[PDB]
Image (cartoon, rainbow over all chains, first blue to last red; front, side, top):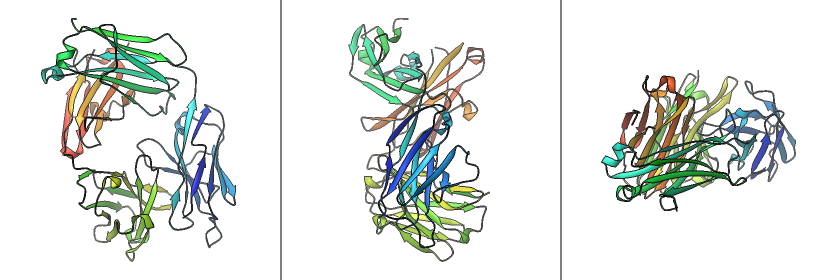
Length: 218
Length: 210
């Protein structure tokens, strides 16, 4: 088969700057009719891939003119002249010159922007869940930048690692931030044995956290 | 306008078969080829094969020969992909894709197949209640993926963060947050709607001050 290899695997790029992604085919992909059927797609999270460029260098109608394609032989290049926030996602090259049709491995375009502190929100177990005998403490850390941020929990002032699960959204297509949820799951029994519950956010750069707390007795 | 409507998600046990569908409209059905593409986490995108409804001719990626079979029914303008001898390796999102023309490219909305011996479990949905205030919805302990979370039936869409599910003790859990002006809550209702296709359950959980 034709192997398509993309460089780089991830491309951090400042908003407004230019970006360039390359795609190398392991063999020739000139179809027997003289054309080179190499396409570029952008896949946003949850969406189907959107066609950007076809036959190496032809911009598909409807596609913004900041996108362009070029290449010859076995090296093909997608360029974005001025990256916008809506341009984040995973870019794929794709060839349908030779069976089997094949995709590159994808390049994730990541927007670089200014630091942003998270908006942090803490939620005790709902009455509904406690009535069912469970106890989850939920902490949202929303719209921050950069993506690397750590969460630590404290119960009655002591650090707590048991029962913590974290999840991150993909980078936001409007403000280029990240968001994260941290969920502390305990038995209701253990939850009712303690009073203070703290969600603490630290960046890897700074030692100053952002904290949110609640006290069960209130 | 050209549209391709795929069948809904499916939970299927290993060793079974499954037939997924792709209903086409808005063009002469027999004049364009339809492709299928597999999208499995950590394996990018893979082209499976195509069928030409004009003559029911097929071409397959060698990888899927003896696994996938494409068929066409002209009366209903529908293409099917059947997968046999199912394993966990077959769990994926499957796309059907019509040959491209000038007025857009034509991908279906995707079908999420989960191949698992585990039974369906509906989510338990809990309200997360306490300028811009943040409310939430905890969607706990369901199987399989996916679930569909919206707020106020989808009319509340900006300021929403719905997080990827994490697997914990063989069940998935996610949460969703929404941020709205205090001048609108609780004076106006805020509800998270959680729809789980495998169990055909939909919950509307109103968020009420504690």
